[PDB]
Amino acid sequence: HAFKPGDLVFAKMKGYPHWPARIDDIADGAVKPPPNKYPIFFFGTHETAFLGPKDLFPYDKSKDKYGKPNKRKGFNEGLWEIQNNPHASYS
Image 1: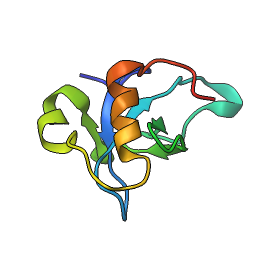
Image 2: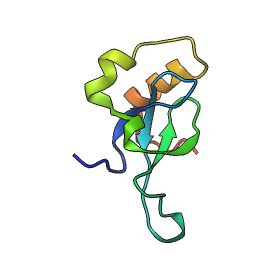
Image 3: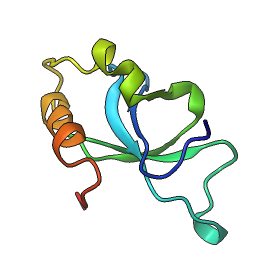
Protein backbone atom coordinates (compact mmCIF):
# COMPACT_ATOMS: atom_id res chain seq x y z
CA HIS A 1 0.00 0.00 0.00
CA ALA A 2 3.02 2.40 -0.22
CA PHE A 3 2.72 5.34 -2.66
CA LYS A 4 4.91 5.14 -5.73
CA PRO A 5 5.79 7.25 -8.83
CA GLY A 6 2.93 7.16 -11.29
CA ASP A 7 0.11 6.65 -8.74
CA LEU A 8 -2.89 8.83 -9.44
CA VAL A 9 -4.43 10.80 -6.59
CA PHE A 10 -6.58 13.66 -5.55
CA ALA A 11 -4.24 16.06 -3.73
CA LYS A 12 -5.58 18.45 -1.12
CA MET A 13 -4.21 21.81 -0.22
CA LYS A 14 -5.56 24.89 1.52
CA GLY A 15 -7.97 26.98 -0.55
CA TYR A 16 -8.55 24.35 -3.29
CA PRO A 17 -10.88 21.37 -3.64
CA HIS A 18 -9.25 17.91 -3.72
CA TRP A 19 -7.42 18.18 -7.03
CA PRO A 20 -6.49 15.57 -9.73
CA ALA A 21 -2.80 14.85 -9.48
CA ARG A 22 -0.02 12.32 -9.81
CA ILE A 23 3.05 11.18 -7.86
CA ASP A 24 6.12 12.17 -9.88
CA ASP A 25 9.52 10.47 -10.00
CA ILE A 26 11.34 9.94 -6.71
CA ALA A 27 15.13 9.97 -6.66
CA ASP A 28 17.84 10.34 -4.03
CA GLY A 29 20.83 12.68 -3.59
CA ALA A 30 20.24 16.39 -4.13
CA VAL A 31 16.64 15.79 -5.33
CA LYS A 32 15.67 13.44 -2.45
CA PRO A 33 12.19 14.53 -1.17
CA PRO A 34 11.82 15.72 2.45
CA PRO A 35 10.90 12.88 4.91
CA ASN A 36 7.50 11.33 4.19
CA LYS A 37 6.82 13.85 1.42
CA TYR A 38 6.06 13.02 -2.18
CA PRO A 39 6.61 15.05 -5.37
CA ILE A 40 3.16 15.85 -6.75
CA PHE A 41 2.18 17.17 -10.17
CA PHE A 42 -1.25 18.82 -10.33
CA PHE A 43 -3.22 18.15 -13.53
CA GLY A 44 -4.80 21.12 -15.25
CA THR A 45 -2.74 23.86 -13.55
CA HIS A 46 0.54 21.92 -13.72
CA GLU A 47 2.29 23.00 -10.51
CA THR A 48 4.63 20.71 -8.62
CA ALA A 49 4.78 20.52 -4.85
CA PHE A 50 5.82 18.24 -2.01
CA LEU A 51 2.86 16.81 -0.09
CA GLY A 52 2.58 14.26 2.67
CA PRO A 53 0.20 11.23 2.63
CA LYS A 54 -2.47 12.92 4.78
CA ASP A 55 -3.22 15.15 1.76
CA LEU A 56 -3.10 12.34 -0.85
CA PHE A 57 -6.30 10.44 -1.76
CA PRO A 58 -5.89 7.39 -4.10
CA TYR A 59 -7.72 8.17 -7.29
CA ASP A 60 -9.85 5.02 -7.80
CA LYS A 61 -11.28 5.00 -4.27
CA SER A 62 -11.99 8.76 -4.34
CA LYS A 63 -13.01 9.62 -7.95
CA ASP A 64 -16.76 9.23 -7.37
CA LYS A 65 -16.62 11.82 -4.62
CA TYR A 66 -13.94 14.24 -5.87
CA GLY A 67 -13.81 13.76 -9.67
CA LYS A 68 -16.90 15.79 -10.62
CA PRO A 69 -16.57 18.96 -12.77
CA ASN A 70 -16.40 22.32 -11.13
CA LYS A 71 -15.77 25.94 -11.99
CA ARG A 72 -12.28 26.28 -10.47
CA LYS A 73 -9.70 27.39 -13.04
CA GLY A 74 -7.95 24.43 -14.68
CA PHE A 75 -10.07 21.83 -12.81
CA ASN A 76 -12.05 20.33 -15.74
CA GLU A 77 -8.90 20.37 -17.88
CA GLY A 78 -7.20 18.51 -15.01
CA LEU A 79 -10.01 15.94 -15.08
CA TRP A 80 -9.42 15.44 -18.81
CA GLU A 81 -5.68 14.91 -18.22
CA ILE A 82 -6.02 12.42 -15.37
CA GLN A 83 -8.52 10.39 -17.40
CA ASN A 84 -7.03 10.56 -20.88
CA ASN A 85 -3.25 10.95 -20.56
CA PRO A 86 -2.14 10.88 -16.90
CA HIS A 87 1.41 9.65 -17.61
CA ALA A 88 2.34 12.17 -20.33
CA SER A 89 4.99 14.85 -20.20
CA TYR A 90 3.23 18.18 -19.59
CA SER A 91 6.49 20.13 -19.17
